[PDB]
Length: 116
Image 1 (cartoon, rainbow, N blue to C red):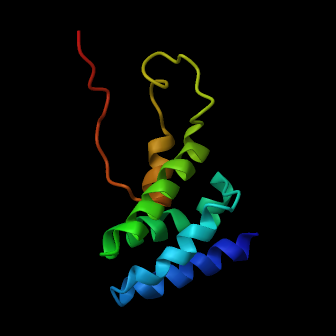
Image 2: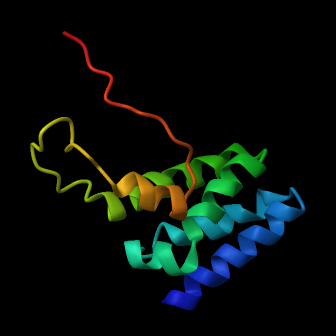
């Protein structure tokens, strides 16, 4: 299903360029039914396409569908939903942020803000 995701990413990019991402509703809806993998995000770069749709769409349903995928897909490279105790919350030295920076580009922050 590699090209399937590529087709969705390219369908989204066309809307992104024209600032008319309302049509992405259908695309993101289908992506919820697709078994995305870390490998798919690397080759199809759809994480970034969906990330772009969220900010290029005035239609909140589209942003809501898209924001859903970003979370579900992020766990693929992260090892999320199967994380151990680590050495801090969900681990320590989580280099997966670099993969995320390439695959999604969903900004950067230090994190690890905890209280005592």
